[PDB]
Amino acid sequence: EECQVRVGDLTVAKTRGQLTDAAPIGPVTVQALGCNARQVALKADTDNFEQGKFFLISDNNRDKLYVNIRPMDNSAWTTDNGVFYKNDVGSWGGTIGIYVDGQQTNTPPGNYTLTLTGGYWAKDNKQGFTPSGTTGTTKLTVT
């Protein structure tokens, strides 16, 4: 199945200190076409994806802090640092959010760039992921 996922580019001003571990301040409206028997998994792009870890990286790469793209409230997903996929199979179409992992710090920031590549997933941990749909660039400015 070809999972067409709608990932919205979200440029909005927040603090990473306001991110108190479990605080969704980047609710991405993800709509997934199909996926009837498929898991949906998110991946970060080269900007904030190092080998298999995603985080909030600054426009000037001054600070990096790991986050989790976890569903706001609708289901449970298997959290990996490289991919985020539900154990469920089917069209998910809902809202996930950026939660900072354990509230890092928030070191005097400015602009943050976390490009999120949409796609589906077809196995478990072995990285059976396929980039599909739209790549949404979540931009986290502090103001």
Image: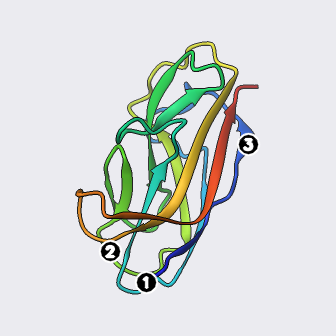
Q: Secondary structure at mark 1?
A: loop
- According to the image, label 2 marks what residue? 88
For badge 1, the amino acid type reads Glu
| Drawn side of residue 112 relative to residue 105, left or right | right
Residue at horizontal 51 percent and vertical 40 percent from the top: 46
Q: Nearer the viewer's eye, disc 1 or disc 2?
A: 1
Residue 2 placement (x, y as % from top left): 48, 80
Residue 141 placement (x, y as % from top left): 71, 30
Identify whether 68 is placed above or below 73: above
- According to the image, label 1 marks what residue? 1
| Drawn side of residue 44 relative to residue 109, left or right | left
Q: Nearer the viewer's eye, disc 3 or disc 1?
A: 1
For badge 3, the amino acid type reads Thr
Q: Quadrant of the C terminus?
A: top right
The residue lying toward the viewer, choosing from 139 and 27, is 139
The residue lying toward the viewer, choosing from 92 and 59, is 59
Residue at horizontal 71 percent and vertical 26 percent from the top: 142
Question: What is the number of the mark on residue 11?
Answer: 3
Give the mark nearer the N terminus: 2 vs 3. Answer: 3
